[PDB]
Image 1 (cartoon, rainbow, N blue to C red):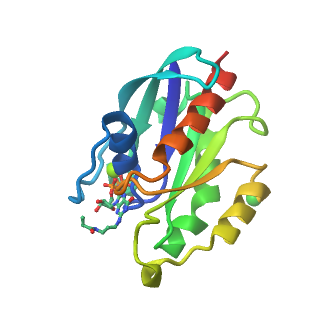
Image 2 (tube, rainbow, N blue to C red):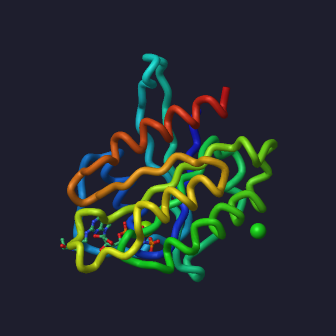
Image 3 (cartoon, rainbow, N blue to C red):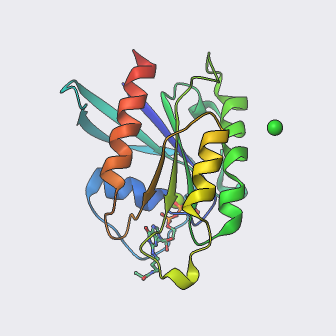
Length: 172
Ligand SMILES: *CCC(=O)NCCCNc1nc(=O)c2ncn([C@@H]3O[C@H](COP(=O)(O)OP(=O)(O)NP(=O)(O)O)[C@@H](O)[C@H]3O)c2[nH]1
Ligand SMILES: [Cl-]
Ligand SMILES: [Mg+2]
């Protein structure tokens, strides 16, 4: 039933976030994602309505990418790394890439969620203000925002409850 797509630059932590939420596990070892594929999780909404969530991981590197999979999606998650300025500045282009290729019926209502990942990292290395993120998140149509750590299992549960809630609303 529920199709969710996760987009964002290489290295931001998409695959890690998916393993955290679906499998409650994490691994330090970078293994580059190639082509799109999904894992599944049975969910229960805040309402105690039940659903199977199909979570799609995608490649961040141009050369490992795929097009069709974007269609169907009931929610789109946009992920940047709080330690990498460029990843953040690319969020709107990931959003627009999705809308161009996704063939969704109402772009101004279609649910996106943004995640800022790697908050567990040392302050010295962190670059993207919460404030900036909240600005970008509003300017893109008041999209929900969540700061997360796949590594330390921080807030990934919260983030994905909204992603679930927003996706079920869009499906039917
Ligand atoms: C354990 C060694 C250590 O201390 N490393 C530094 C800790 C940095 N913290 C941290 N926090 C996170 O929440 C987190 N998520 C993911 N990473 C790391 O970044 C690399 C990329 O992970 P992927 O999940 O492979 O990223 P991606 O899917 O977007 N890449 P693709 O688009 O597929 O190329 C990886 O090293 C992961 O461990 C985090 N690090
Ligand atoms: Cl524009
Ligand atoms: Mg990956």
